[PDB]
Image 1 (spheres, one colour):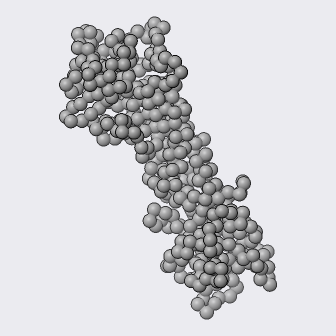
Image 2 (cartoon, helix red, strand yellow; image 1 turned 180 degrees about the vertical axis):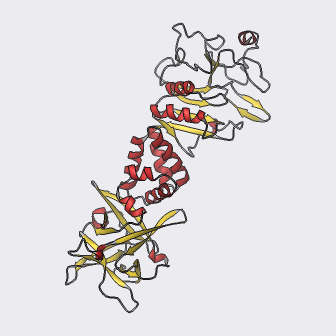
Length: 424
């Protein structure tokens, strides 16, 4: 029988594994008694290996850990490698892989790191892993499962109820990178850690891993964290927020932009007719009534009109070198904004509309920034790296010329921010 094969079995290899002197390791399941639960005292348990067998070498590959507690079925024995058939080191027992309940042995919310591999993650197992991992600073690493498995689906769901979430590309210390047995892993971390991870993936331009992260976050009760990260990204002048929103918009995740990003992002990303209002001077942009000798038109804020076809624009979005870039289209004339090749005596450049649109100076970055509750955008020419501003001086009609600014527009959203509104 299973019991008798276990009773019959050599004791665990405590040369290659550390002997943690766990009192319930050499006993079967005794959870019917008021046992002494670990951890004892105020700290967390360092490391539980769920379905672990201790450090197992096989065909030159390593699985398991010499210093973890190992949750396993009560009669389970080492499966492979030289220790095959021995007893499991530091073994915390469960009745069955079905019940997978450690509540007699391990206190709720008490483990720093849970690793899990080899065994199946049933719903009960996922729930037990979530029960023991500490919500505020826990970490769960699932090794060798496929991302679409019922195993990972059970785990992500139970961890999300507790406040742990997948981190795509989450970097592990060297001692959690020893599992050369497995070719895949999936890391779950605490709410604050994932907040920081996803923010830094976006500011770093790693949109593949940012999209993977946010999708799992929103799908597993992480909406508070998503909202906080988004707020940081659209408040602090991060143009990678625009690039992140673009990839969400085009790769199947419109829900996340619709539900968590400022309403303006939908106008921007779908090339809808918009008004562009200089916040400081409060004037909507238009093009000049007349052309110059090159058939181009100057760009102006209008001192009175904020409704007519003359103040309608569209943003054209394109992807270049891991960034979203924009062209700014005037719908009255079907002309594209650029900055003058000639500077004035302050180094500033007049803004012009042209029928043509194939130069780098036709392309622009948007930097989302917030003045209290008002979402704004800084608009910066990609070739000249100048942010747009309206002239401190009015003309005879009360209109303001639009210039590229020599000098950063980042220190000051009340001066250099634009409001984007729907035109219709």
